[PDB]
Image (cartoon, rainbow, N blue to C red):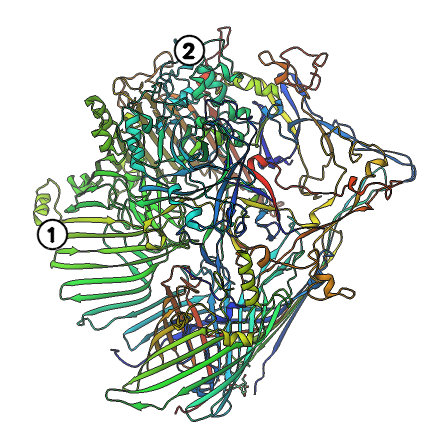
Amino acid sequence: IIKSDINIKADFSLRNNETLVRYLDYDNNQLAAGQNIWSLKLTADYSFSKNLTAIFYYDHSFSKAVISTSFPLTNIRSGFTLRYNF
Amino acid sequence: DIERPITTGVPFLLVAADARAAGLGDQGVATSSDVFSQQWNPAKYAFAEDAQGLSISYTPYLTDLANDISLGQVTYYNKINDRSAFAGSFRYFGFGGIELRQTGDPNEPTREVNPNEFALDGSYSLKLSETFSMAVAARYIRSNLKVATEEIDASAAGSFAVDVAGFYQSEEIAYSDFNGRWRAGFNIQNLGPKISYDHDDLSANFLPANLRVGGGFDFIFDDYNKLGVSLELTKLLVPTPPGPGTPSQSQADEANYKKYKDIGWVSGIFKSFGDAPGGFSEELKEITYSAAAEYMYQDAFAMRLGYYHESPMKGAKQFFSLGAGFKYSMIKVDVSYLFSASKVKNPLENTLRFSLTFNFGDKYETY
Amino acid sequence: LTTNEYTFNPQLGYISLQQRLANDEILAVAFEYTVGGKVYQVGEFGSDGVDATVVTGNNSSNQAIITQSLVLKMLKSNLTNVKNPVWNLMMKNVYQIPQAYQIKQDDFRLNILYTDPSPINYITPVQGSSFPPNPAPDSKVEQTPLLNVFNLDRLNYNNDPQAGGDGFFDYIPGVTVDVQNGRVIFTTKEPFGELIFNKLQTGAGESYNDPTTYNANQQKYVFRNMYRNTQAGALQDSDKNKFLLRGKYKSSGSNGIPIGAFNVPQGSVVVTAAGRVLVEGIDYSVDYQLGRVQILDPSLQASNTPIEVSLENNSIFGQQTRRFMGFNIEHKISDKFVIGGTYLKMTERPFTQKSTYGQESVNNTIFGFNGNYSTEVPFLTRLANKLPNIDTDVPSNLSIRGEVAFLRPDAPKASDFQGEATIYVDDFEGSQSTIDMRSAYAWSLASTPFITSINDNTFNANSNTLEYGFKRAKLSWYTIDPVFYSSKPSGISNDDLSLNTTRRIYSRELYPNTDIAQGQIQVVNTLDLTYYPGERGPYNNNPSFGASNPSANFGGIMRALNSTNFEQGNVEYIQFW
Amino acid sequence: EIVIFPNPSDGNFNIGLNNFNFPYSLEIFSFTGQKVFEKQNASDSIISVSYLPSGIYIVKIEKDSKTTIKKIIIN
Amino acid sequence: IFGSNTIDVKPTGSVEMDLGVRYTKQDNPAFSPRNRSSLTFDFDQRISMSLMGKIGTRLEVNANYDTQSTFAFQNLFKLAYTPSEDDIIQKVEVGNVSMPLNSTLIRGAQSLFGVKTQLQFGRTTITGVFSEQKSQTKSVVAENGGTVQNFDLYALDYDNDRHFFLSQYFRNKYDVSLKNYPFIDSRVQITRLEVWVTNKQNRVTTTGGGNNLRNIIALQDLGEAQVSGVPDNEVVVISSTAGFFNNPIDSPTSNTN
Amino acid sequence: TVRFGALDLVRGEWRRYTGTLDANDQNPDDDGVEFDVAAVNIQENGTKCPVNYVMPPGVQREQLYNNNTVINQNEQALAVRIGGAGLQYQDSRAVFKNVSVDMRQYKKLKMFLHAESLPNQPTLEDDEMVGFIRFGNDFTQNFYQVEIPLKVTKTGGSCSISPDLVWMDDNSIDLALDLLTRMKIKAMSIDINSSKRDVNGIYYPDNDPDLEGGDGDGKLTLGIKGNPNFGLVRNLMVGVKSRADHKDIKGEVWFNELRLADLENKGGMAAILNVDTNMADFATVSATGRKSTIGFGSLEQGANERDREDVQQYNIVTNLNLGKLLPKKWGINLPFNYAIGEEVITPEYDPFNQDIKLDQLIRETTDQAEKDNIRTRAIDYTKRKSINFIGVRKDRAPEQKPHVYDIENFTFSQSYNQVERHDYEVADYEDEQSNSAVNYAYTFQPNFNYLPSNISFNTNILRQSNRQQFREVEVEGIGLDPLYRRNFAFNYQYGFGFNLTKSLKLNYSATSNNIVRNFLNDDNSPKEDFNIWDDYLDIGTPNQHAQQLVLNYDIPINKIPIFGFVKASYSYTADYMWQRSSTAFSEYEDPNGTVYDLGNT
Ligand SMILES: CCCCCCCCCCC(CCCCCCCCCC)(CO[C@H]1O[C@@H](CO)[C@H](O[C@@H]2O[C@@H](CO)[C@H](O)[C@@H](O)[C@@H]2O)[C@@H](O)[C@@H]1O)CO[C@H]1O[C@@H](CO)[C@H](O[C@@H]2O[C@@H](CO)[C@H](O)[C@@H](O)[C@@H]2O)[C@@H](O)[C@H]1O
């Protein structure tokens, strides 16, 4: 009785950043700073009616530590969003 | 000022979460059946006029300062038969997202935390007689207000509670000048084991066990106008902490507090009626009251006025409340405002509470 | 520092930083300058200084690294010492005009006044004495404005020299004014110090560096301690901070008057030009979205008249709840005569029952009676028609509006102490702030200490060998992790958690009178230091450690302090429970 | 961007301005909505409000037309 | 009491409601094992509703509730009950009311929340209000355009720890050089200057003017010669100045001094 | 095992005052007196050994809402401990604070004091320790001192002592500020070197044998030194002094709830009258008269924000359309604006001494010259006058051919503003400003073309004269020498554009500012007897001159049918500026006496 399209959008990102300090006269390649963050955002839209719609969202981001001053961080925000228009 | 207030865990359970009852002076135990009748009296869910109902309610804190610091509520009721109803409510007090950062790095993955407190409850209401109904509710309360750091554990504190409610709605009785209707209600709620925020059996806090008894009357004019006046009395079922001393100098207070904290909740419910140097006259100071009048026009416009008074020696929360309700086709919108009359700054001042309910399904005749 | 982080005066040889160094920061400089055809250098630049590193050898097993330092000039030291000449390098004649960014001439007024106790812009000699006789024209003190006394007024509008000045502050963008940052710089390095001392000097027996030789006029007016001492230290010289730099500046930015508010209610803006209220459609216009007021009256634009704009801004934050009540009568005697009887009351509800100074609440009442009478006067029209070349028929009108108002103010009954309206100058609950030191991870192993003086060899702190660490006994500093109390780890019993050295401390025990919000932390995370004097500490190579007296050993931790200026912060004591 | 040094602080924290026009207005508000801290002509990064009782506080930073509201924790 | 029974109070806009879970895991070894991860519940509301209509051709309802902006002046709610013009009561306003006064000595209030009523006795108009005021009065003074800002500093309130003389030579030349300002009796032209501070950021970046980190030794007495009117102990900290100087008594500051 | 339940570096708002408060000692960094200042709390010091901390009688804890919970706020008192050697006979130790407090609207200053003996030390007896508040502009020259001998709370037994006995009413300071005002008035007649003053220069009426009633307070001892001002308190000090002759006293004193009480809430009156008339679209008169008394204000104004002044102001603004007095055939737009007005302000408090009522000071003077000086110097009088002829133009005829020599291209604007003032800071203030502007603007309508497309040219004559004479507040005998600022200027900028070719475009403009220096002598001495209309149409010496020139050329190379695709476009902006140097440069003089011209820029 209820039939509608399902719209899915997926966004994956992977960003690596590195900062090296190099000495010319001897091997002293110093790792000054660094980042390695990969994120994934899934969203799925389903329209129950002309006014009521549901959106399933799933964000999953992981930041790996390159230098010890930063800690690995995992963030997962998942769930549903109901929107009703008038 | 306040003299020895009753301290309980998760006090946000006592905050009114909907605009309809907010406009009626924070009472709903004996008002007409509505979708928000879960925090106040689930027993009238069996008296609901509509089959199915959903409701979203918003109470902002620090309205001017910042958003996302609010108490939201989602309620859904469904009466399968003429005699029974299943309801489910979810109250969520939250501060929104908070970013934790220790270094000034522009590129730094930081931790976003949302301290919160939510209660998810489900109630079954069964109509015993044609005018009386009972209800049993089970509630799970979870508190995650603290933030994980060093030497601090942010493990959420959980607890369970049971609510027993009863609602009586008389038939429409004709009088000399009108044909009104009588209502009564009682609710003993938040009955459960103590909640330990530190996850230790030595340190625990009483759940805000509450007893609410109320009664109301509707004057019905021309069959299209209603005026309902309701009065509710509320009493906490938690023992009052000792004051000066009831046996060195600090040792008496230490012994009194040790005796008070070593009391079971089941025994604490019965101990609440007394356990003070004062008598019955001072015992009546433990009861807060609320009186409201709600005018209904065409069953689609509602103008609600209410007055809520606590004892000046505890809580000190007295105010007047205004509320407006509009039903367009199947959607009811309620707005509530509060004028405080107490010396302590009410955090709900200058706050317009919002409530929005949708009703769907077939209609049930009212008796 | 990047060139964006500082500026400098190429002629007067001083620098101004974007970020001030109110801490133990070290400031070093290298600069080269030209005097005519001569070039002088004082520091050591990165282009002409020694190389940062010199490496000798081919492989890391036998390489030698030589890290070389640049020789610079010290402007601020690691440790503050007001008796060293490096302290004198810090300028104390620059004053930052608050919230000023682009001060310009004709839009900046500055005056120097002497408040004792009222603002007076000249200096009187102390009773029983007089200012030095026959002074130079540039050294006049008696009956002289303080702009001339402190060498800030010797030029006219066009910066041309004038005999006694034009009475206005001299605006030189390179000498007395920093335009881009809104700073005022005195023409002397110590205007309130040696300059006023020289103005009041009567003989060679008075030395500015010897306060005991002052002549009872330098004893009153020479505030030397603001230059020879820190500002917190100069606070101890109370009778001298009487000179006041009082002024104003015009902030425009763009066209229109910035009323300092956005999306203001319509009809809440009242504009008064010279005691008369203007008309919102004729004399001025209001841009409510952008919060602008544009004066449309041509006479007022070229008037230099102060215009007062009073609006109502509803972007209020942290304000008490104010109740506004009252009535207004609008009786109509005739079709052109109206009488009004407005009465209003505004009460404020304080957050607490104590009102501190400045954060006060009002309970004001205002009631008034007004009368309006607007008529049409054909006589004026007929008189106008009698004029040579006037033949108009537009009616002439008269209007008289009288009004009387009475204000009865009061304070709310909530903020009364024993029946009287009370304002707390100091209830003493805001004093004595604390800086927490019991964070376990902030402490590290300490160096060997001296116990009476730098010459005391008790714990072998003066040793340059391994004996330096011979007296270090074992010490552990920690906070017992909540896993021991909540989720009992294997091998830990309940007897292990009840010893007064391992048991969990609750705030209700240490602070029985303190109220904690429900859901917050009810436990006290104590900093536990377990000291074993009979056990060998880290990096201790004592051949006979167990054969010595354990009471002669030490166990220590050290910590860095974020705020190093105890005098400015008024760090009063170390308090520990 | 506005940066707040350790969010669960004891009352002593810092601001993370990006080396712009230094005069900014800082206002710290309690959960009651009361005004508990004012700071105009502000340029010092370190903020000492450790006399405030524990809880969450709202920090408003006004920098020219820029307005920012952040939440901090005092524990 | 009402003109009719038609109730066309219609709501427009949208309402959003997010229910989900937030899982966070930070691998900080100093954290407790109980703080390994945090699994909380996210509940969010984005009410963006308007409500406009009439009740019985007598009540006008205008409401706007938007939980995405400042509630001080955006969330609006007005009920206006206007009976027939022949009645004693002309208007009853509930919610966002205003109290406009055609007065100069007594200013009315525009942004209020409360009850406003109006009565008409033949020729007398009585307007009563009881509300809470949602704004504050702000006054500015402007001359020749922009507003006037007043400042009052004291002598002790100088801009400290921000302004530094480059040398004792410049400090002792400052007063004499500015004797006849705006003319400066000095030919000094600072052509190049490098400034070094204590590094506590410990951040390496190529866009911040490059990575220029050097070991630094800063001497207090570097580049200082004697001064004619200042004793040596006020110019240098060196304990013994015997043989320290090798330049005349008024030489400009230089490395060879 | 040592467990720190708390470990803090505690910093205070009240700074320990170093330096002698008594002239008999004159060596503060000695005597071996340990002087400590800290705080005592209800949350931390409820079990204190000598006396447990309790709130003063009638004082309650503040209550707030943290999260739906009522939190009792901490109650704190400032504790001052004197130990070791002890205070000498007249020595005192105190803490201080920098404030900005106006207490002119409150009648009482109240504060709780408590005294106790140090444990394991000789007992402190009653009336030996004296608690004092010293407030004013400083602590050594200009201050009120309020002293009270302290009754000592008896100890030895139980640590818990009732609040009525911890904070005795005999130790509570309850000062009437009119007593301070009367002390100030009485000390006005006391010489600085008088024998009635102490070694510290403080005048105590209680110690005056020739004064009846003393300071008017039987419990407090009041003193004054140097004309302080409680209308603006910049320095506040609380401390302990000794009165034991042959004894060194030791003990701890608590200070609590320093507050102002008994607000003066007499209202105020205001009246406003407006007469607005218009006369046949030719005349418009607007007269306003306001008169407000002391105490009036707005609803939102606080105790120190309401009007402490009597204001009597009027303002008449008149607009005429003089162009309508001429026939409409040749239309002239000649509006004339005349705005006169003045305000007189009488302060509630005399501007001198800043804290005594003007009428009270006038009554208790007994010298006609001094009364006249006070009344005249108190008044703040302002007067403004403005004459405006802005917008003088001749409108175009309904059917007229535009011409370059037409008078319709000219616009005239005259403005004259005069401000007279005299107040507590200026005995006489003149501010004149005359601006005359003539604007010309014509645009043309349809080897290379030499006809300009448009020509613009405007001239300005700005003259500002400001005479400022500061008053001698002490006597109206001489006053200060008047200071003159004059800004006579003549400005003119013109501009014109050419369209020599369909591609070329040449916009030129030149601005010039000259300064008129006819008010100066041969030396750098202004002339007092000068009128702003002396030589109005005088062009002064050049001061600044700027030229701007813009060339745009589309380079029509497309004419040659080999380069028809090139779309070249050349723009050339040229700026020149000449700035006159200050006279300190153009006539700089060496110490040798020779004069050099340093030139312009
Ligand atoms: C646990 C709760 C789960 C959530 C319950 C959602 C119920 C959704 C039902 C849609 C509804 C309620 C409106 C609720 C909106 C509130 C949204 C809140 C937003 C938050 C921010 C809207 O129906 C109304 O709205 C209009 C839409 O604008 C409809 O238009 C049209 O709508 C479409 C034709 O229906 C067209 O396709 C569309 O083209 C048109 O436009 C109209 O039909 C009608 O006016 C009508 O209810 C009806 O649908 C069924 C569905 O099977 C419900 O079945 C129930 O499901 C369980 C109940 O959950 C019960 O257990 C179960 O026994 C029971 O069989 C019944 O109730 C039934 O009566």
Q: Quadrant of the C terminus of chain E?
A: top right
**Label 2: chain letter:** C
Q: Which residue is mark 2?
A: C136
Q: Could you say which is closer to the camera, residue C519 or residue C324?
A: C519
- Across and down, in percent, residue B266 comes to 55, 77
Q: Residues within 10 Å of mark 2 (few under 14, many from 20)?
A: few
The quarter of the picture where residue C321 lies is bottom left
Judge whether residue E36 can be spotted in this image.
no
CA–CA distance in space, label 1 to label 2: 70 Å
Q: Residues within 10 Å of mark 1 (few under 14, many from 20)?
A: some
Q: Residue at x 60, y 53 (%)?
A: D7
Q: Could you say which is closer to the camera, residue F590 or residue B181?
A: B181
Q: Amino acid at mark 1?
A: Glu
Q: Is residue C37 left or right of residue B119?
A: right
- Across and down, in percent, residue F511 comes to 42, 30
- Across and down, in percent, residue F573 comes to 52, 35
Query: Where F577 falls versus E110 (above or below)?
Result: above
Q: Could you say which is closer to the camera, residue F554 or residue B259?
A: B259
Question: Do callouts 1 and 2 point to residues on the same chain?
Answer: yes
Element type at marker 1?
strand
Mark 2 C-beta to ligand 1 under 8 Å? no
Q: Is residue F58 left or right of residue E88?
A: right
Q: Amino acid at mark 2?
A: Ala
Disc on the earlier residue, 1 or 2:
2
Query: Where E5 falls versus F260 (above or below)?
Result: below
**Label 1: chain letter:** C
Q: Which residue is mark 1?
A: C376
- Which label number is shown at residue A73? none
Q: Is residue C517 left or right of residue C60?
A: left
